Amino acid sequence: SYKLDPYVQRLAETVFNFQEKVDDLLIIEEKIDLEVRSLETCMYDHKT
Amino acid sequence: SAVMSATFAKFHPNLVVGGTYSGQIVLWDNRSNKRTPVQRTPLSAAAHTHPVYCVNVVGTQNAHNLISISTDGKICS
Image (cartoon, rainbow over all chains, first blue to last red; front, side, top):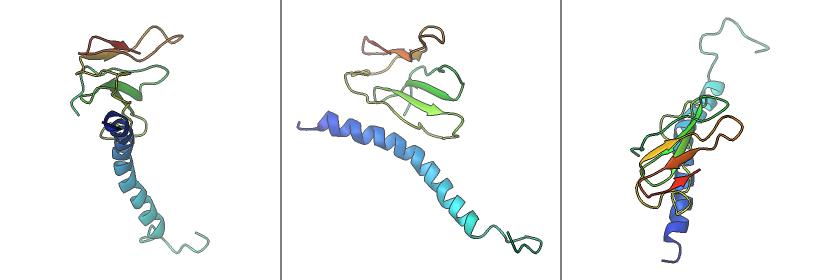
């Protein structure tokens, strides 16, 4: 009974923010992969 | 989790909120496009300690507070 409700609620708020961060983490990894390989069908890009 | 009568908020129709099953009014911004609940409030004595019943807005835009009267006999705004 030291921190059941306190640490549980802290992990709950960070858990919901982490669920949003899970979907956003998939989107973040997708943004990094897109920025690493987005010129797969470009028409002779040099400065780009 | 299965919420209990969620509703909207003020100044935009994106950051909605609603009393979830854990005991608080879980909020989420529709402009951020999040599938599950984006940020859930603390479900402690501040929110509904017991189950949830209903959530809504409070007053006009001058004092629109997210007020939820749950299944714990409390209107937490």
